[PDB]
Image (cartoon, coloured by chain):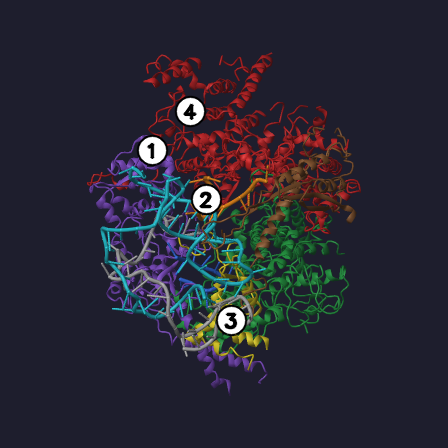
Chain colours: A purple, B yellow, C red, D green, E brown, F cyan, G orange, I blue
Amino acid sequence: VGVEDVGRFRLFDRHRLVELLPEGLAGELSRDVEMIPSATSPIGVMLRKATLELQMQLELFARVHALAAVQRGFLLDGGKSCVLNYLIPWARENNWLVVYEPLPSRYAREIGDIKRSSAGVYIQSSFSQEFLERLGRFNRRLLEELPVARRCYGQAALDGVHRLYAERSYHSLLEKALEKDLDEIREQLDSQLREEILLARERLALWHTYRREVSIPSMKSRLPNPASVWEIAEFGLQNEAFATQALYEVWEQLKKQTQLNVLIAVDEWNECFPVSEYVSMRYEGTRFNGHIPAFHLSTPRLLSRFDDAQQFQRGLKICATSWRRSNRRDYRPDLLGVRQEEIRTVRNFSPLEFANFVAYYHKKKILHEFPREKLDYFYMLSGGNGFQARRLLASLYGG
Amino acid sequence: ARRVGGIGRRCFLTLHCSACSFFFQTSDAIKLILTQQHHILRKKGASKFSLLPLADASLLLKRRGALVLRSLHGDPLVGSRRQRGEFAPQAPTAEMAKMLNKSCVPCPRCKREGRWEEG
Amino acid sequence: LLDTGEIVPGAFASVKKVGDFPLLPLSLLLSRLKERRQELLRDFAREEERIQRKIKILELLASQGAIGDAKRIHADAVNLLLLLAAEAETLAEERQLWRLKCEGNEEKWNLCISRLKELALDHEDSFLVFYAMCSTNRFDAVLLPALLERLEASFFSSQALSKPLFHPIFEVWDPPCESFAALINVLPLSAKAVVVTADRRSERERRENEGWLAPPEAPPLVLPNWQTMHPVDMEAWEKKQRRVVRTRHVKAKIIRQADGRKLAATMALHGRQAIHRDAAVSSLVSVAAMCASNSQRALRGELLPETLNLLAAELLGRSADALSPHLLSLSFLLSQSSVSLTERLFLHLEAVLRGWLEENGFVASEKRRKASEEQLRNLPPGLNVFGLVQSDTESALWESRVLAALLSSFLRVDDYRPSLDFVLLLSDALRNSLRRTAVLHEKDVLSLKETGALLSSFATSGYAVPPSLMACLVEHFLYDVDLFLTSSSSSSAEEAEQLSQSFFCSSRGRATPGDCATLLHSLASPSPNLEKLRFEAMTQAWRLVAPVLHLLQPPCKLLILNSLQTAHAPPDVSSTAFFQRSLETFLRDNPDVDSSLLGSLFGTQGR
Amino acid sequence: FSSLRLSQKDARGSGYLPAQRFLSLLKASPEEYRSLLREATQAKIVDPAFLRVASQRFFALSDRFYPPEILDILSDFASFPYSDEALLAAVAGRLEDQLVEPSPKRLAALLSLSARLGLCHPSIRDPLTKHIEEKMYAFDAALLDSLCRTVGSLLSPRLPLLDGLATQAQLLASDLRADEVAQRRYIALLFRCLEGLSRQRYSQSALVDACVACAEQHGQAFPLHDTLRAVAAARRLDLAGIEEPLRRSDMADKVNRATDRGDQLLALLRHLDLLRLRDSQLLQKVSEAVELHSQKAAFLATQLPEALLHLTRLAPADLRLPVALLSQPSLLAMAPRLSAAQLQQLLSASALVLFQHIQRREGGQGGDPLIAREAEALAKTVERFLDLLKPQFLSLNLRDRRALKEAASLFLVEAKGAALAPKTVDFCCFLEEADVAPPLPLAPSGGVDFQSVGLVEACSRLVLCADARFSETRNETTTCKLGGVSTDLPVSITPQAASSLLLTQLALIRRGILRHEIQTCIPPP
Amino acid sequence: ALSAYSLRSLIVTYNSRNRSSMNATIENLKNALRWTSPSESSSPSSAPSSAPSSAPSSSWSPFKYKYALRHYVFEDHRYAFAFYDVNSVQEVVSAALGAMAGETCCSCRFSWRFAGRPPVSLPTPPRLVPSSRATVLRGHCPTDKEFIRRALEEEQAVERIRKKLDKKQLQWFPGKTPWAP
RNA sequence: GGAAGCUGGAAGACGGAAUCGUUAUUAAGCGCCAGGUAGUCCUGGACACUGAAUCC
RNA sequence: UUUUUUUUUUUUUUU
RNA sequence: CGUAGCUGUAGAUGAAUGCUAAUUAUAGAGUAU
RNA sequence: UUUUUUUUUU
């Protein structure tokens, strides 16, 4: 390990990798592992130079907590998702709470349920249960031991909206109600100044009382006095009502207190902004043809806010986009939340790394015969791209 | 492959706004001006009040309302069969922008005076 | 080891460090080669090719020596450079014979460059040339970029670790091995900074100090004539040719590659690991130079502030014994960047200054003489500093330059107050008497190029220069002007001043002299021999800029014109001779600037 | 975040930064204008000429700045208060369009407009005051507390505006009423608000009863550095009962809780400046602590100059004598202190004390002077303090130089009155005739004469004197002599107000011809 | 001012319908040169403009089912010339028109230039002392190359602007606009 | 007369039989306009890309 | 071009 | 430019496009279901 | 075969 060891493959046990990554492999690596005929063969991942720069930052961040260390997430733009197969397993081995989500779009382009509400945020009861069930597979034994704060008890609505933001939707309804009821006091001049001021004072008294009686938020009365954060089993029991309120409660809880280092990795982040496959009546004439934007849903919105990374006093977030699901085009980075100083633009594989990749497949009995004479010839054909290299060599005998 | 706008991602049907950030096609322009007819009539100051019934929101979604919108929108993109080669249709936003700005129609996003532009 | 038959994952926790400790010249290496000659000989069509050439060079190296040039002036041009490079470094009635040999080596060294650049060097000869220059401290701003590409393409080649050594015997007696793979990995940290801190600017770059310059973008101007005009009947012309010649206009442009930046990024990461190892102070100076880059590293990744913060944290926690000697190089590089951990770092570095000067005898002239020498050549490996002081005749000639640049470095900071007012007076008085005895001659005179570096700092830090004028009476006018005219029409005046900044470059065009006029204006800031000398200096420098006051940068022209219409300026200078009609010329070109309020920036109001 | 900045060191000392970013500003895109403006904010030196150039161009380029950009640009003006007559026309031309029912802009817009010159009735006050009184049903707790400090600094308020915020706190505070939930949440939102409204001599019946502690046994309210708010609110016209439940407390009578050098002396001293309170028999114990604290070397060059300047007023509350502790017992070798940052603070302190010495028994009463030897010792300090400022004059910001002129002109009266050695060079070169960026004054809206206003250069940096009204309007025991040559009530706290007002009258008579001046215009404390 | 004008350039173009007719014009133009008062005569540059062609179609003898066709080709020729620094207008305009022969029309294009304020500055330079304290080819244009480059760039700019504006105002049924009635 | 939305249960998976001919940028597919002096064709004229096989 | 891009190709032209 | 490569849907037993209460465009006039 | 922006979410 170090600068001297760049572009090498690290062996991984088949059984150990599954336990460390219960959800699955990071990226499209599952398509390349099935090609190996041997079932007992190990899995190798190349150590690109982009991982060395990122790994060093995490080392200093852990030592400080025991303004020099970074306190914001990064962004990989341009093999951006290849590093995820080596950075996540390593961090998890160092007692780090890592949130794994390689396929966040599965909760937006599949069979589900939507229920409109006054808050204007659609919820998914069916997909809300799968988020916590998959996260607890490997992150267990730590959430239960972690305590729970008392300053963030129950200030979230059913759809995960804050109390202050949820009650604002009813401001218009209450505004007209008070205007019609003012005739009782308006109809009983005196100095032309105090008479008008006294009438206005009645509005303040009535508004204060109206903002605390009509609204009846649900303060998770099912659990009066919690003791931990992993002891919330009632969320898994009830799904029709208590599906989204508990999802946001854990999200807010992991910002205030600081006991353990955390990490969040969201892959394929370029397919969360575009429109979803849902249909509704929220279109702005011809903007969506009657479709629900992906960022307007509950689950996608939770992982579609990079400007909030500052509140993460425990850790930080990270995302990468390399697939061809949508044309990147200009891909404005300034109007999204990230800055120009936090974008890691990787490049194509160097000739040195290209040779190692070809030799790696030989040990796996993937290719038939790859003469050294044509080793450099194939570099110009595919251009050294990883996607074009594996596909070109797979179709043909290779070399 | 079959993208909208071609290789150069052309857009000859949308109009930008100087204020805020919101764009819409010419199809929605007709509906916006008709819906906000009360503000336009009062701004200036029976034969004059002929389009009052069309201001209804539900009437536009009916069979009768659908035909009225299509009548005004002549589909400028469609033309004669001889209009080939250099004689190709251009962006009709030049005429639409003038009417939208002179009528002083408020923007759905923020209530403002004439702030539309070609884009 | 795990029970599954794999490496324990706990081992891969931290990142390893780098070495680069040893550093030797090409002098002692040759001595060992000449001794181990009988042991090196112990070691298909290609079998003879790799043996015949491989032994001929061994016997020769110890093309007829260092004589028989010109006629002789391929690996021939490469091996010749070694003899000359090694001969020069040997130095580091008697002055007559020595000068004859010293001059010949320098003249021959430059001649070999012309033939070397005309042929593209191979991977096996590019590194040898670059390494030799570093030892001899003889770089080239034109040749460095060309040789940097070869070292990069081959480094990332497929045959890097598997390929054996180069056949020059130079690699046989080397610590590293595995051909270029590990050879560059164990490169001294001193030489690593060169790649990162490489100037890629061309000669056309003159819009910073010289003035305005319009670059051309259309060299070829193809115009037809009457004798070479195509006939009217062009249809038959094509039928009278063997093959197609004329074709549609299709020309391919040249796309610039990384140009060595790809290799520089990898080298930058090595310096980061060599910070928390508690190494020597001399070795740590190289890390700062790389982090203080301005044209290669840029700000792509968010690692620059992190590396700088770590370097400052370790540097602060050190003894004064090892920090006192190393003060000019560290302060010069650390002052070029701003970070949060700036005030705390500079406070520690200021305290040692008080004791360093007091112990050296600064307010027994041998104590101050030896101290300066170590800071000028011994400490700085290959750095080129303010005014080009870079790695004594009678008195106070070399030590003055060292002290001149030190003051400017502390006043350069942009994070907090540079220093205390009391320190400025003490520092100013320290050199006040020292410069008095600087031999009141020869070419060893303080040029305006290095003089302007100090005057520039005082014009931006908000600190007014003291009334002391002895520094201005030992510089510029004294011999830098009279000597220039002594050594060998209307249009003739312009060429006289233009020739000054041609080869020797006594001044940076309009960069250094530009601030000279502004400082002389503001000096005695209050107002209801110093007065006599100020008038003579202002007029002398004004007449040397007016003739060429047509091709200068607009930003520079404003400063010159601004510092003439002031109360401090001498009278009878703004008359209808060269300035009255020239004032409206600038205003007409740039009418957007204030016309009535011309003297508002630094006019009769001083500041 | 990890702040980092790189300097243009391409040629290592080529060109001139102040000049380089001067011509490009005349022709640049709207985005580039904002980027260059921030450079001067963090810069060391300030150029008055460059400030006017940016202001003039802002009005022309106001047609492409988004509403968020205008607020961000206005925010940068908070430091070094500076403005031009052409700046008001630009902001007034787009303030109406910015009214989109904003929740937070009610405070940010009001706070930014507090300084410089505002309160323009039929351009700015009409829309802001009309929109703030009807939006009292959505103000956050944090915003309401901050609004108290804003209204306090205003001049010539109206009953409808004051009453709007008075009733807002009564209902808001009741919700929290029903140890950290009250000790730092309930009491904090009570005394802070009462002081704000008390400045405008306004109070209602349904606020005093609720604000005061109902139970007299409610001890341990606030520390020594927060209890002064309750005392300052009272002692105005007829207020009492809030001070102590029966003038017998447990943490505010026996030398507070605990006073020491552990970062506590400065905190209490700073709180006494913005609160109009006189050191009574119990509050005078702070002066004694200075004698021992000044002995330490660390305290002599870390907080000594800051404390002396920030509490120069009310001489019989900090120093035993005006010259005893104001002398230089050991300052001969310790005079230098961070070039100019703290050295200038000593000059102002020596000037305010001079005014108190003269205006003590020569027609003002309220004390008596000391022996004539006191003046001799005082002059020995100022003579050696002004010289050190000559080479460090360029290392002062716009705000630092603005206040220097007020303290510099004072020495030009006593010296010639019938002395300082450097009074003919330093005091008659720049300190007498300054041309720094002159900000606009804070004028009321009671006169209703904004259609005929002007500007004249004088000590208060600008004034209201039009050509039509030129020399014509603005130009018993406490009214006869106190309203004449003094013209300063002993509300606010007069030691500073008297010095600024007297200098303004003289500066307007020496150069300009302006007779029959009606000063009035006494802002709240 | 009218007196301050000067003929910057004069682009002379030809349009001939026959190969022989175009060749005669070239020889006639050359003969008119090498006879002026100045040492070097005005030598314009050559610039061919391709050769447009047209050929309609018609059915072919009547009473046939369109089994054969007969085409009628109508070729054309063009030629363009460039001028720079035309000091003598009489010796250039007369020569160009006098070189015609047969059905060979012409189309000239004048180009004038007006000078602004004559730059007059830089008087006798100041001076002080220390205080002691030809090459003309046969068939080539005599004008400087710098002048041609400055004028050539202007021509390329006008052509681009004209093509862009002309394309915008090019639609069938002129005067028709959408939803105008 | 041309095109378009909506609506849609017009008639067809028959015949490996037989008649019209291609001398390779041939054959087989796909895409564009120039003229026909307002619109107005699946034919004719005319250009460009992918482009196999056989004993001819 | 390790602060560079963010991508299919036509039937006249850089004389 | 079209079949692109690439990539989502149903690895269509069910993709045939004519019929018409109804409008788009040229024209002086092409209308009635 | 379909992207965000002028700001009111701990």
Q: Secondary structure at mark 4?
A: helix
Please give the label number shown on residue C195. none
Comparing labels 2 and 3, the label whose residue is closer to the camera: 3
Q: Are marks 4 and 2 in contact (CB under 8 Å)?
A: no
Q: What amino acid is labelled 3 in the image?
A: Ile
Comparing labels 4 and 3, the label whose residue is closer to the camera: 3
Q: Are marks 1 and 3 in contact (CB under 8 Å)?
A: no
Residues behind callouts 2 and 3 on a single chain: no
Question: From mark 4 to mark 1, how far is it between C-alphas?
Answer: 23 Å
Question: From mark 1 to mark 3, how far is it between C-alphas?
Answer: 67 Å
Question: From mark 4 to mark 3, how far is it between C-alphas?
Answer: 77 Å
State left or right for residue D509 relative to residue C217: right
Q: Are marks 1 and 2 in contact (CB under 8 Å)?
A: no
Q: What amino acid is labelled 2 in the image?
A: Arg
Residues behind callouts 4 and 1 on a single chain: no
Question: From mark 1 to mark 2, how far is it between C-alphas?
Answer: 33 Å
Q: Residue beneath label 4, please? A: C124
**Vertical order, C83 against C333 (above or below):** above
Local packing at callout 2 (Cα closer than 10 Å; few below 14, some 14-19, many 20+) is few
Q: Residue beneath label 1, please? A: A375
Q: Secondary structure at mark 3?
A: helix
Using the rendered image of the protein, determine whether residue C565 is visible from the camera's viewpoint: no
Chain designation of label 3:
B
Q: Position of residue D387 (x, y in %)?
A: 66, 46
Q: Residue beneath label 2, please? A: C300
